[PDB]
Amino acid sequence: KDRDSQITAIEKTFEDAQKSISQHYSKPRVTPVEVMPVFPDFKMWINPCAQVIFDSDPAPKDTSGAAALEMMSQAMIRGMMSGENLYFQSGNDLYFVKLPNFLSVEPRPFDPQYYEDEFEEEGRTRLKLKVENTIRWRIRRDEEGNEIKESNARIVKWSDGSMSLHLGNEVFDVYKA
Ligand SMILES: C[S@@+](CC[C@H](N)C(=O)[O-])C[C@H]1O[C@@H](n2cnc3c(N)ncnc32)[C@H](O)[C@@H]1O
């Protein structure tokens, strides 16, 4: 397809991912128990669980520990760049995603002006992998000075105990291991 059409379709995966998830696509009685956006990274926010103090009367706060630290692993980056693999964080947790040959990730934030049109049935499976089936993220600056990170992708845990990966519109059955 045209370069413009690829980019328009990629941008749509972003819009589709923000659409409200309310019921399972094949099981309309099944409802979402947790929705986690997927931001591929080699970095983690972590809270100390406790400060150890030498004063019996400390500066009062709601919660033991402290504000979050950012930590990183050089290991996590190989994998996302081979497009075979990815890590992401949700709450205090680290998830590892093992990618099948029919999905991919792009680690660098998406910017359309640098998007390369590689297409002047095994060329169609290729055009679809990179437009519909590639996990991506982008990064925006508001008119109110806010920085907005957006992802293509969502991991959903369902009311029946199952899990799916939403990539834009498309749905992939997924399993916890
Ligand atoms: C997290 S689940 C269910 C949580 C519920 N308290 C439970 O554990 O049974 C549904 C919620 O996830 C959020 N959500 C809905 N659509 C989403 C989307 N496209 N991307 C990220 N989060 C979404 C909304 O806040 C929605 O109410």
Image (spheres, rainbow, N blue to C red):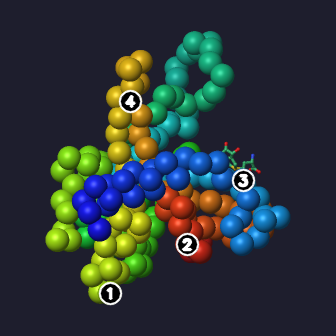
Residue at mark 3: 22
Q: CA distance from mark 4 to mark 1?
A: 40 Å
Coordinates of residue 60 in the picture (x, y in percent): 62, 14
Q: CA distance from mark 4 to mark 2?
A: 30 Å
The tag earlier along the polypeptide, 4 or 1, is: 1
Helix, strand or loop for disc 1: loop
Residue at x-position 50% and y-position 36%: 48
* Badge 2 amino acid: Phe
Q: Which residue is farthest bottom?
A: 121
Residue at mark 2: 172
Dot 3 surroundings within 10 Å: few (below 14), some, or many (20 or more)? few
Q: Is residue 58 above or below residue 72?
A: above
Q: Nearer the viewer, residue 128 or 95?
A: 128
* Badge 4 amino acid: Glu
CB of mark 3 near ligand 1 (< 8 Å): yes
CB of mark 2 near ligand 1 (< 8 Å): no
Q: Nearer the observer, disc 4 or disc 3?
A: 3
Dot 4 surroundings within 10 Å: few (below 14), some, or many (20 or more)? few
Residue at mark 1: 121
Dot 2 surroundings within 10 Å: few (below 14), some, or many (20 or more)? few
* Badge 1 amino acid: Glu
Q: Please indicate whether residue 112 sits to the left or right of residue 90 in the image.
A: left
Residue at mark 4: 147
Q: Nearer the observer, disc 4 or disc 1?
A: 1
Coordinates of residue 130 in the picture (x, y in percent): 32, 68
Q: Nearer the observer, disc 1 or disc 2?
A: 1
CB of mark 1 near ligand 1 (< 8 Å): no
Are the residues tagged 4 and 2 within 8 Å (C-beta)?
no
Residue at x-position 17% and y-position 71%: 120
Residue at x-position 35% and y-position 34%: 140
Coordinates of residue 143 in the picture (x, y in percent): 38, 20
* Badge 3 amino acid: Ser
